[PDB]
Amino acid sequence: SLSEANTKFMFDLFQQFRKSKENNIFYSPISITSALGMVLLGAKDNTAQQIKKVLHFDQVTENVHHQFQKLLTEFNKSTDAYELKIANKLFGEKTYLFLQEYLDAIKKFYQTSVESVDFANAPEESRKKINSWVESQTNEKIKNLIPEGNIGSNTTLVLVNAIYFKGQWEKKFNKEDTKEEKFWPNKNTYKSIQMMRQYTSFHFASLEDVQAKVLEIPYKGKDLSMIVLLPNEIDGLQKLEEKLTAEKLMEWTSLQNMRETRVDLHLPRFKVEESYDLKDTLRTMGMVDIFNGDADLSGMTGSRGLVLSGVLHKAFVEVTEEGAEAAAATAVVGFNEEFHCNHPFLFFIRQNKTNSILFYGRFSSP
Image (cartoon, rainbow, N blue to C red):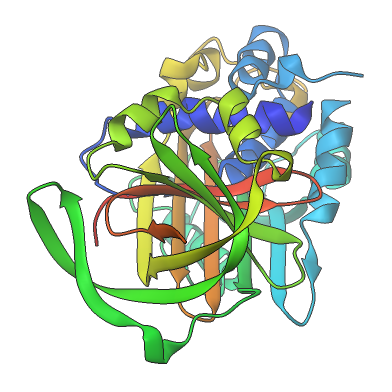
């Protein structure tokens, strides 16, 4: 199952991300999968086999690219209550020729469009053009995706994925009920925060065992939901993080294993913005040939010689009384019950029909 593969890669990412100093974590695993999927399509031999393993695409069954193409289709839908959109794009050096085969394949499986830019003579201005396209696909929430240092006059390829979601809560919060309260990042310390509050019935589950609770907060239309995992104890997050695997997430957070239940939901207004340099991270995870001289990306060009210089990700979420807005992008460069979220919690945004986790995060502090 592909949904499962993507969710496993999501946890493999999370364990790496835990090592940086940043308190909050927020990223789109699907955006990253999509960008690396476009790289895989042009990879060969061992270069390809390492990518497949990192993405868990070697564990999907029946061609994976076809299954991903079906997913991409589902992720482009707007109603009156929400917008979800995803796009893939290839920016190549103007004078540089890709295999028609490779172009047809990314067009077909990843809906990728192609734009030619002048990296050779204008690498800085090319950088800024890619960064603006990304703004343009993210309601301007992802700015400066690719910082200086990453594009040069020898750059021949930047593959980019952008994903954007904005949706209304099915049951909105009343701004009149929002109040300043303390948020405790640790047992013995606090920061002020605007706490939204409502009493309503939601699918709920108590996970007595990791000493946590789970809540589903639907978006209007119920195509998407935000799932939140709240440790029972102020300091219990570290255990929950150790025990939450893809298999456990799938069990605990399915409708099947939750129940409609009335909850004083207290959820803070919050905003998270984070950046990731993914090169060394993916290297650790198993993707080595692609970043060095062994690289085989001859499926892109017809011969070896292309190597990836970087992989960058940036992500944004904001939660308000009306709903939530979430965005991310990835660049690859080549050459009765209470649920009170007043201490750290995990959250994610899921597309319910496909069971896909589009965005995943940890809120540790305002």
